Image (cartoon, rainbow over all chains, first blue to last red; front, side, top):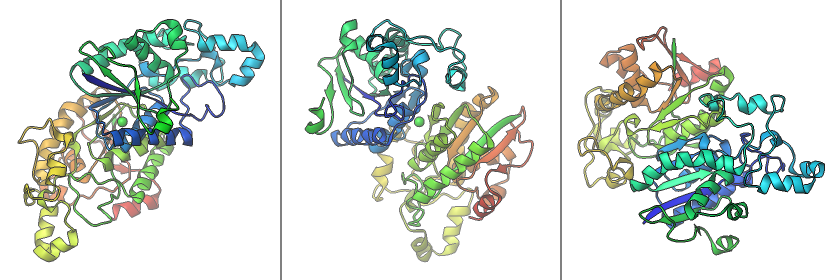
Length: 240
Length: 243
Ligand SMILES: [Cl-]
């Protein structure tokens, strides 16, 4: 049986500022960093070892990867970064305050483009305070006019995530390499959905714990031979 | 003109313990870490930006790479790690104390297998304290019996470094990608020698500053168009060159 491990990053600087992050490169908050440490300790204690790692091109996710490798003393591992594992692009809501946004458009509206499977938030216009900050960033200089999103629905996110998983990650798993993916909530949801074959409703209600190692054991067809497992003290694995 | 940047890692835990490190995975000391931060900011202030990075598989070098990327806000850069950029393997001297070693073998002998060009140190015997910690480390699971050294002369180090530079790095440079190499003294010496076409004696007289960005400007033949340049306060540079 193959062993895959996922880890959603913890609290970011904009998280405790209650702002929508999306593609904005917010860095981890101290608690977010600490969270990745305790999650790292967990893998170390469990004795896990990997062969290759995948992550996005966003600080909060990458730093999480670094903190873990350090903890499990595997900084030498090959690392592959890709925009396809990025958080979902919150379009024009980027930078706004989640609270003020609900008070302005009504909770119902906000709830929608936040828990919807195909409702794209409004696009990010050229005047948005973060338009050149994200749209004009070397990071994505090799992306086609399309590929660079103006906004994304979880469906959009998944559509551009899986191609990578299928073409880049699956091959490594089939080659028997222990993979470690350090990414975001929405991009990791796409993998989980594909793995467990969940419905659209199913994933909208699924909230992956942060900074906690998510373990999957796949069969010869990359199918979870069991529900996802968490690592760490019961007082914590319980909380999940 | 192409722009290449090199950076030798700073003080390690065994450095302030005055022990020979070689392939032992010693981590950076706090000063070594701070030393990288400063170098990184130097790059930040200068406005440098890269496209890809190369490093070894040793903590002290990698951590240096991380500290720099963080400082120049380029953590998203593609990173490639390789044992071919590793420090020179100090064979059986690994772990020993440089001082006690000279007192037991005489400074002349020690000076030799430290500033020599083709004289390797004593092999690391299977009864060595770090023989398994190093030889049996997963990091090298894929190396062939030959590839995995028990000791290396600076010449040995270079012999296994350049193949990578030629096959892996040069192509990226020719593709116009701004490269950043974070490695060790002996492995970086191999690149410098190849670049400036230095003699064995010349290379043996070269001590690369640590934690200081080394900038090269190459022509279409990947040949320097000016001497190497250093980045940082004039004092910072001065102080570093002396060590
Ligand atoms: Cl990395």
